[PDB]
Length: 56
Length: 50
Image 1: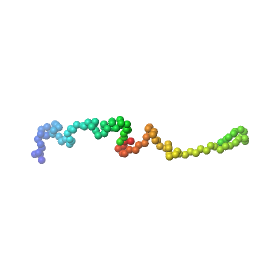
Image 2: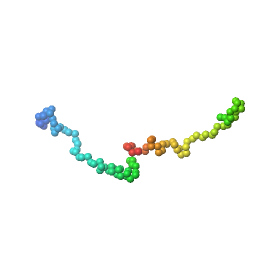
Image 3: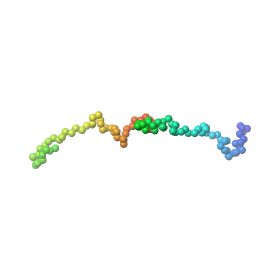
Image 4: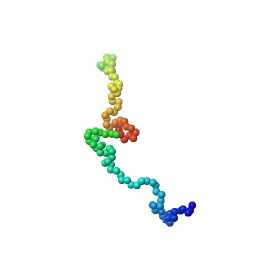
């Protein structure tokens, strides 16, 4: 079992940096979309200005 | 109550006015309709939608 100790963890013993550690899983960075392009953002500014009061 | 009060034997008596006290027609005024300061609310749960 000690034949497979992956010998660059033992070189930086107690000095491990980020690429030698198991990270929690997660996707990459996708940018947040425009909140103007939301499905009900502009139409709430248009249907109310026609005279309606909206709720729901 | 009374209708005339001169001396303690010489008074007269009339019945009081009839006063009926009951609820309104169709229960008007039981419920705050069109009072904005305290409105009722019909909404689903996830209740951000009065």
